[PDB]
Length: 220
Ligand SMILES: Nc1ncnc2c1ncn2[C@@H]1O[C@H](CSCC[C@H](N)C(=O)O)[C@@H](O)[C@H]1O
Image (tube, rainbow, N blue to C red; front, side, top):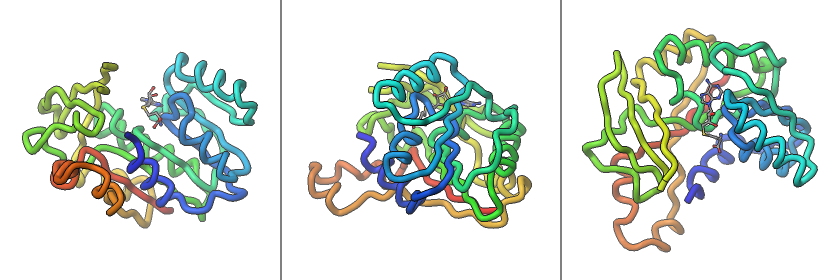
């Protein structure tokens, strides 16, 4: 069910050959490991969860890849160096305040070579629970509650549960600018004609009219 998401992130990333890559909020390492498979020179993954990093390391042992993992809170992260690429699939929606969203963007900037780039996948600020739930596409959004200047959502995968935050487009763009990224662009998920042809008609209507997801590319 992650086909669109994978396609969009690797579209944003482009050619990884010979690059150094920091995969933030890496989970068991899905994106970092695939980025290595596609030719990256070196991949480091970071996650706040000790359990997730324990699985990430077990996965790297099982296929013998050279990924290195760290247990760190990205918002409050010990410096790890500078990379050609920072990948952040489902990092920023875990920032629990606008202040912590802004700190995460500053950490990413400090982690980038001058010619590097951030590729991110996060919650679309324009998502509105009343316009259509996302359960049909893999994420059952259970509720939507005002949380300071943003919104908090409880959700679950179709049944592992989790909670995340939907900050406004203006707050994301201020965090980006104030962290020192001189260029950014929002990327619509890459729903393609083949996806439409292989699903019942109108299956993707809510995905198009009320997408939970968005891509984001930022450059110093
Ligand atoms: N402050 C923080 N710093 C680092 N990781 C965090 C974090 N808050 C949440 N996470 C991690 O973010 C992950 C979101 S799930 C995304 C996992 C992976 N990038 C993938 O797409 O497959 C979880 O594994 C969670 O432990």
